[PDB]
Amino acid sequence: HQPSDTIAGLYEAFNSGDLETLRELIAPDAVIHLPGTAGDAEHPPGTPRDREGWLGVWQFTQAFFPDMTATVQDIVQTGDLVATRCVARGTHSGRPFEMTMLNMSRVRDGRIVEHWTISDNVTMLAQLG
Amino acid sequence: QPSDTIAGLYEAFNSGDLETLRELIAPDAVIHLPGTAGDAEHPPGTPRDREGWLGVWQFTQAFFPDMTATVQDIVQTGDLVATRCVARGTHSGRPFEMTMLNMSRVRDGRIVEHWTISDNVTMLAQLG
Image (tube, rainbow over all chains, first blue to last red; front, side):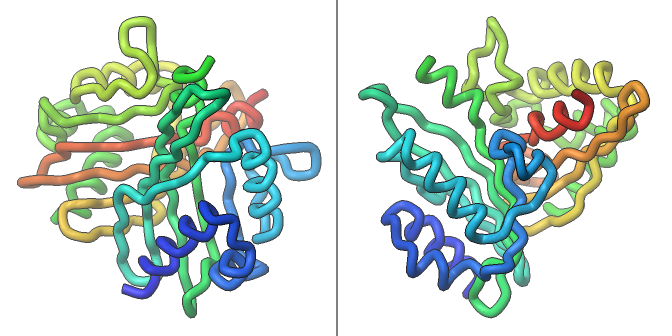
């Protein structure tokens, strides 16, 4: 049950802003598949990022939603693959939101080497405006 | 096994097999669809039942008639199965590949709870 612990540790580390732990738990050359909403001028929607590309997108999103946190609701493991359902909770200008996130991660030697994630952005927008 | 149920579900969606879909999904299943599947009558974040889900899926089938969903990775622990799928098709001569992530609870060989989200923005970018 080591891969499960890695992924639980990842979301803890994102919530705390713990860069050191993030960089231990994610390989520098990990293949990170972010959703099309994270697409931009240099990286069109289908294009994988590396670790620091992912942490860059995370930091941008944190600037807009400084109190956003992720809590793991379900976790399943088979071999080196871990899938998770999380709920991202925050407020925008004092109005609370709850958004589902689904993730799939490959873990090797206690580090993330591949990750897919998608968030329910439309449901979150509906709750705010 | 729960893995077999979920593999059978995506086969049945690909073939348009309503009878098998209704065998594999309980009528009272709790289906958490993304906000994109929200509607005037069903606001975003409201769960649907089976027939609500099959209603949304039938619209999506009619809109992308050559789209298929293929299970790429599947993980199982107890009654929970998560899957990563790729939805592939050519729509009006433009090819597309979009990731889908799903999580299902299976009980007595039927889906009783399901969460799904698709990478719609990536798909739209590939078509326009």
